[PDB]
Length: 175
Length: 122
Ligand SMILES: CCCCCCCCCCCCCCCCCC(=O)OC[C@H](COP(=O)([O-])OCC(O)COP(=O)([O-])OC[C@@H](COC(=O)CCCCCCCCCCCCCCCCC)OC(=O)CCCCCCCCCCCCCCCCC)OC(=O)CCCCCCCCCCCCCCCCC
Ligand SMILES: CCCCCCCCCCCCCCCCC[C@@H](O)O[C@H](CO[C@H](O)CCCCCCCCCCCCCCC)COP(=O)(O)OCC[N+](C)(C)C
Image (tube, rainbow over all chains, first blue to last red; front, top):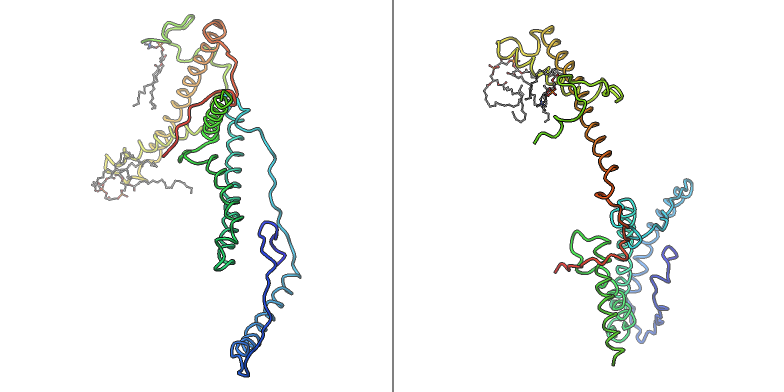
């Protein structure tokens, strides 16, 4: 339905064929479907209608919490505990959001593999490539930090990688 | 081995210099005073138990005197202790101020410019 964003959770246009009977025999599946409909789906729908009638009477909402952007750990001087505290809390919240991004991408991948049936190896390549890009980025940022991770250790990992990349590019320029 | 015995202008046996009166006295509900009163109460109860008297009931005037004595002495103990810590901090700050070449203020770096070593956990 419209409850969730179809841009973050997309799906193809859902092509389904029309029934083309070839025999005089009655299809027991469709009769069972009519029986199921008129014994199960209608009482359940009525119950839900009443429940939502009672819901509409008392309507209240909640709001997603928004967080400002505070200075990160790079612009905190070495022993300033308050800047360090706020930077570390911000880094932790960002780590949580990145975990959820990888989760969304993995959900897409799984849904594609199930949906595409026998053709998943070709029809889910974009989902696989998207996951590969996200996984590579997430791995660079947080892998090998260990328990007792922190923004300072993430910064040290990034700086080590940046040094290696700079030196590699410099010796490639001499080639 | 004797850091504050030789301090200048110190009266031999005062226990409470006059300069100590510039400091805020401990409140009468100071939790350290309450603990001293609890110590006095435990002394009263052990007193009853040793002399084979009912432990919580026997001498109420005696237990009151125990508690009062402990609280009374603890008040002055706390005053003297807070005063001695105030002396320590006063002297330390004055010494840091008069010897600036021993306590220099060096420019501190943000973590963006300090190169820290990374150790992977694997
Ligand atoms: C960290 C968290 C907080 C911790 C708090 C601090 C620790 C506790 C406080 C310590 C001091 C307090 C008690 C000292 C005096 C006790 C002496 C005694 O004999 O007690 C008997 C006495 C009972 O005897 P009885 O009623 O006359 O009749 C009994 C029979 O006659 C028959 O009696 P009996 O004499 O013939 O029986 C003899 C008995 C007698 O044996 C004893 O009574 C042992 C007493 C040893 C005193 C401990 C030394 C000082 C305290 C140090 C605690 C150390 C803590 C750190 C870890 C170490 C663990 C010990 O010995 C034996 O039977 C042999 C057993 C041997 C087993 C080994 C255990 C021995 C050592 C265990 C020590 C455990 C800690 C103390 C536990 C509480 C004891 C009352 O105890 C009491 O009834 C009174 C206890 C406290 C009541 C007062 C409560 C305050 C008022 C109520 C209102 C609440 C206030 C808040 C208001 C709220 C708003 C509404
Ligand atoms: C197990 C706990 C220990 C109990 C200790 C016995 C407590 C009861 C003793 C009675 C208290 C009265 C003693 C002092 C009253 C007035 C005398 C006063 O003028 O003395 C001054 C000094 O004051 C006393 O020294 C303070 C005594 C306080 C002792 C309690 C501290 C215990 C440490 C932590 C345990 C908590 C105990 C809880 C209390 C029951 C003199 O200063 P000064 O002449 O220049 O120093 C001589 C020593 N020098 C030169 C080498 C430095």
